Image (cartoon, coloured by chain):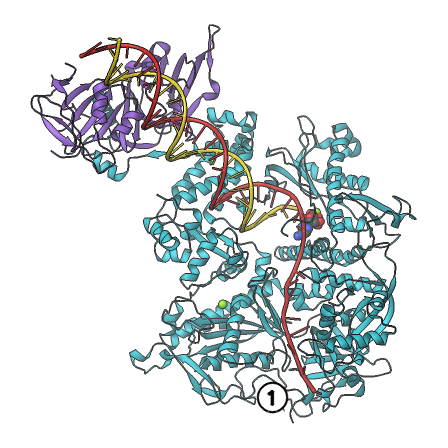
Chain colours: A cyan, B purple, C yellow, D red
Amino acid sequence: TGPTQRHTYYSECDEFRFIAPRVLDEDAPPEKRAGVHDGHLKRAPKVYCGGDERDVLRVGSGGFWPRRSRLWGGVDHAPAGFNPTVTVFHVYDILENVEHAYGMRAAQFHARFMDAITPTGTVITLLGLTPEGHRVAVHVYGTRQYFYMNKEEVDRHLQCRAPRDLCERMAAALRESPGASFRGISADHFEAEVVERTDVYYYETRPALFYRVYVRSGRVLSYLCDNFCPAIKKYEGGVDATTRFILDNPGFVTFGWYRLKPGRNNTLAQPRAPMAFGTSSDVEFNCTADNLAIEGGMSDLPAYKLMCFDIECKAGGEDELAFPVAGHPEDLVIQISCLLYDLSTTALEHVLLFSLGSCDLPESHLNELAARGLPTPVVLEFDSEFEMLLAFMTLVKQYGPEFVTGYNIINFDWPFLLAKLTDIYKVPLDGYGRMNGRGVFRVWDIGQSHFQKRSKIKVNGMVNIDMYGIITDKIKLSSYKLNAVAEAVLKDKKKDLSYRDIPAYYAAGPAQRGVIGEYCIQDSLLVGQLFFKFLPHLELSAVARLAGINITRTIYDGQQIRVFTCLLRLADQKGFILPDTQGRFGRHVGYQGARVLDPTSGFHVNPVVVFDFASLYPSIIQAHNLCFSTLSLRADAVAHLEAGKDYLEIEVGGRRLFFVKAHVRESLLSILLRDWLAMRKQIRSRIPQSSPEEAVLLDKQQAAIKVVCNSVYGFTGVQHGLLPCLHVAATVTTIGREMLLATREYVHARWAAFEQLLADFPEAADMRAPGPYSMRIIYGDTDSIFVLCRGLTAAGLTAVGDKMASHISRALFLPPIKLECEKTFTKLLLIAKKKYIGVIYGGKMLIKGVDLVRKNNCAFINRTSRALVDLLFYDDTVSGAAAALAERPAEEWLARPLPEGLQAFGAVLVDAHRRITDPERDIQDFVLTAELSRHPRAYTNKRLAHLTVYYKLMARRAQVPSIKDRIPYVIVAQTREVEETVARLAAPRKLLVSELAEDPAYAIAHGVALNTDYYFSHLLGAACVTFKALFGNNAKITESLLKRFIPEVWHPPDDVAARLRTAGFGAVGAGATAEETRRMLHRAFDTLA
Amino acid sequence: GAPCQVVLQGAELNGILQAFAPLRTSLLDSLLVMGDRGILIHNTIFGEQVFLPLEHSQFSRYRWRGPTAAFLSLVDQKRSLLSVFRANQYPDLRRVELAITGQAPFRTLVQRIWTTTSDGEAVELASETLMKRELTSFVVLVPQGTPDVQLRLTRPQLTKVLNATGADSATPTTFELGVNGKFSVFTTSTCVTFAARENAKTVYGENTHRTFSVVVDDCSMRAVLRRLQVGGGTLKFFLTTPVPSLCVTATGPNAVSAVFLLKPQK
DNA sequence: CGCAGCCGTCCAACCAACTCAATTAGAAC
DNA sequence: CTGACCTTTGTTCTAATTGAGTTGGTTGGACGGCTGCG
Ligand SMILES: Nc1ncnc2c1ncn2[C@H]1C[C@H](O)[C@@H](COP(=O)(O)OP(=O)(O)OP(=O)(O)O)O1
Ligand SMILES: [Mg+2]
Ligand SMILES: [Mg+2]
């Protein structure tokens, strides 16, 4: 008989495709060592470990890896009489599935559950762990999806006369579908009720009658939304059953502690019998929502297990040094590292190496691991690729890690594995997650899709966190290779192994395969350290709780769904419904954004105070009660209210809009924001008591929550989004623009004279510096102004600034709007809009927008630019000389030597011009980078350096970059072989920059020379754009003056000399003594004339 | 102050301009070289060497100090210090001055310009002041020794000798001075002759005793000699070297000169 | 006095430099 | 009495790079006019 539903993972296997490298036959002839065996073999898959040997798929006593699994196939392996009491459990994940009563006949389910899935129903499975470490699944019965349609409309269109009629007309529509995939659907599969609700979109909208239609399947709901009566507007048809479960049971959460309890008539949750289990769990329960409640007190995580894994591959074709491609049978996975951690404790518990072929780890690696008190590695040895991959999947099923991590596992590792398991071997993956079959196990690349922000993985009960994703969001680097990240974040240098090196190590015998093993283990250990520094699961679960969505959606599914779910929570409890209006789907902007003030470019050596609004756009939404529900586009809507007292009237984009005030109706967006603003405060509250490392981590968490608050504004601005309203978005930016200008005009009126300031702040008297007093706005962007405060001292302006900010705020705006005094500069270089460099009153340097802090540029030019900046700001002779340049019009410096103090500034450039030519130059200092922002086909301009390097890599069969990867390149010198190459492939031509781009590894290997002219002109370019501000923003003058620092030199060409020497001895200058110089010039004039 | 000074007052200025007017934005990009003896200007035109020796005689005040100095004529690689001497670049120019300052490499040159504005007075063309720094190192290759023979081609017969030259790169051309002094320049296609003496046939000559014939592979010779508005000029030959050359200089007290590499065809 | 050659002026051709637009990266908000 | 899959915060700004078009300047060649010589 066996289990109620079939397990689809492998529990027995008698025959398989055997593929393995011939170089593992240690006693084979030299002629037989190449390539791979590939044929079928009839035996059970085997694993070797420490001289012992076992079948891969056998469960029993002497296993080689840990297990947390109760059932295997149909057999139960729990001790006799195993039966734990469950009261409290922690849920980390939620599934949605459909159960059919006929499929469940033989399971001994109580009647209450059978009624909920007759003839079919959706079941919601909570996945979790008890505090004793038992894996639990709770199956929740009785949740139904539903949507709304306007009753008058439906009545008119279909001629319905009772709710039962609409159910009959829906059943008809389903039956007559092409593909006929809804056989058996009847009116009783639907329930329709008349209710009163209101559409959420404008203030004057009256409540009306809607049919609410309950549907027992999401597949059915999808079809009805798309295809049934398309003229009729539908509401909330896109909401999933999980969301319905979470929102209809107030207080329930997608991540956290629950307890089981008696229900509505003293019903209790039913334990499932093991042959009725749906998942790999210790205990399973059937219940309804009445049997669940949240446990407020419990907050710590239980003993979840984290797996960190990495794979290594070997190409097996004719070119050993091609990058491996998973679709080729001979390009094999050779090793898998797998580290198992307890997330409750941070402790590493197991270190497993899977290895095709024998593998002896070097004694030094074992001693190192022992010294750090880490578990001794268990090495698992396999004869063929299949046996190793099956074993790894067997571990994943039997151990069931709730969290899985790695580095670049979503773009490389999982795709490579799953390709092999699907295409080479024909293994079904739907049973390898938590469910025993019919579950999701997929990767989505970005591919040709115009929409997708990122690649994704979903495995039905398993949270995948790629640390490559996490790191790119938290640290700014030009490269995100793991050695660069390890250097930058963990502060240690890993040695590294290139894919070019692996094929020669592999062929050498067991010891060298051991060296590969060490590299895999070390890589996985680094990724573990990164994981436990950033602790991403805690940040993600906090957001998941607040948004009302599961943690996997919290990782992969964007900002809009977070906002939408929050809005849905509030809408429901106020009587509003949300229109779907998304039946389909330009390149330009939808509305006017922020005002940036024209900067007074220059070098400023008087103090500058920066004022910035805290949480500007959220505060505007809150202060002025902005919402869908509070908006009107008509004056007759607000005719019965009082102007100014009850509503804001505002011109926005040439329309007169109206927003009702909060005592007339509260904004749903205003309420939504409260939780997220609170969450951000709670993080920032902890910064001053935290360590210097904790403080940096907390600052980044803080900033991620700010992104959610701003995405509430953004949500309204999305054309073709889930619930657009460009009127709201444009209002927010309009009000912001007004506030910025108002703040400037206030400061220019109130404190024009020192008298006025001293009248407002008596402490001003101690702050008076010697020259004339002035306070003037020299710059400002969106929500901040820069006030140049000549005549006052920096020491006091910090304190006075707080008071000024308070004063302005209380004079001009409505709470929660708060202007704050952010910082004071002692020196400032305003370069352009969004580009400035300055020093804060403590001594700290701040840099915004300039190439010195953009990730595209090379290390040589960055380090030189930083040196020039340091001289302007921290060398008194240079700062003084820079301030002197402003006394003359810029072009006057063309006809006069510069102030002498700029000596050291010029000296830095001459040194750079020297060092750039040295043969001992480190090519890595010259590496440029750009992101591959999109699929290479979607580019219009195709002459790009990174695209040039992209196609070269593809044609050389190197590792091809993924979309959204940064691509490194160098610019090479055009030796004639380049002209030959590019002309040959395409069809005195000076090649473009994009045609000289090259891969750094190739350029090293083939000794290719760097383009010194490009790099030095690009270095002067960088200096020029950064120091134009000292010369009136004139780039041409800046360029000219900067060139006057450089040593010019002139010579005849070599063959020109080889000729001229024959007749006419050019001893002019270098090449002869000053005596011979004057002699030869005399010698020459008197014959040339 | 200003250890080196070079000056062109109006009395001497026209001595330069009379030599420089035939030059039409042709010499504007050049190297300068300076010592006690005056200025040498040098440039390559169509891949062959051109020189203008401006002797310190041609100047109203002059002083040199320290080692020789060298400067490129362009400033910002756009404007040029030689501009003053071009045509009517400026309608009037009462005087011009070069001053050189500082020490060793890194000496600073300024060129200063003054113009009559009627009113009995002259004023600085201040906006046109040019400042240039000595180049730190240089190699320049310059000619030497007494020429082997000279012919004095007045403008008409210069033009005839010049028009008889070939073109492209394939076609041959040769200069000749055979016995009896025929100066029979020719190609396989075209021929001319002029009566060398140490009526209108004659070319006045020096050291014509030595007789020779020699081909030239150099293209664009005539192109260069037109770019330069060569208002007639002496030809003088250098033949003792393993590669020979022919130097053409305009007829006058001071002159642009261009040096053309001949073939070592004996 | 007539014809031929040389010189001067004007117009066209060719080459280089500068400007403008659009795409892209990547930041600041 | 049985099947499923597209996604998803906003606008403003500078700078590099590439490609096309426009403008200006200079040089070369042709034709006409004037002067000199036969
Ligand atoms: N990522 C973003 N998406 C959308 N709007 C943004 C984003 N960043 C900034 N803005 C807009 C809305 C912000 O309210 C406004 C000003 O931003 P900014 O001052 O950086 O933050 P903030 O004022 O919202 O928070 P705080 O000032 O406390 O950091 O610019
Ligand atoms: Mg890897
Ligand atoms: Mg702000």
What secondary structure is found at the residue carrying circle 1? loop
Task: Give the left or right position of residue A613, taking residue B156 as reference.
Answer: right
Residue type, label 1: Gly
Work out whether residue A266 or residue A538 is closer to the camera in this orientation and state it.
A266
Q: Which of the 4 image quarters holds residue A35?
A: bottom left
Please, which residue is most extreme toward the bottom here? A1
Q: Is residue A278 visible?
A: no
Residue A478 vs A71, above or below: the answer is above
Numbered label tally: 1
Q: Is residue A359 visible?
A: yes
Q: Residue at x 56, y 90 (%)?
A: A60
Residue A218, percent from left and from top:
72, 74
On whether ligand 2 comes within 8 Å of the CB at mark 1, the answer is no
Chain bearing mark 1: A
Residue A186 vs A1016, above or below: the answer is below
Residue that mark 1 sits on: A73
Q: Quadrant of the C terminus of chain A?
A: top left
Residue A1051, percent from left and from top:
30, 35
Residue A897 vs A396, above or below: the answer is above
Q: Quadrant of the N terminus of chain A?
A: bottom right
Please, which residue is most extreme toward the top here? B120
Badge 1: few (under 14), some or many (20 or more) residues near its Cα, within 10 Å?
Answer: some
Please, which residue is most extreme toward the right here? A640
Work out whether residue A187 or residue A617 is closer to the camera in this orientation and state it.
A187
Task: Give the left or right position of residue A701, taking residue A522 as reference.
Answer: right
Q: Which of the 4 image quarters holds residue B134?
A: top left
Task: Give the left or right position of residue B101, taking residue A396 as reference.
Answer: left
Residue B184, percent from left and from top:
13, 25
Residue A8, percent from left and from top:
60, 84
